[PDB]
Length: 18
Image (cartoon, rainbow, N blue to C red; front, side, top):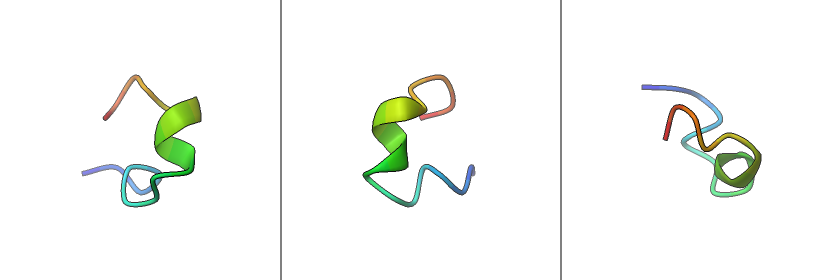
């Protein structure tokens, strides 16, 4: 599991792992 995935904020700018 990714780290930026735990935060719904980063998830937006990180839609490649989530």
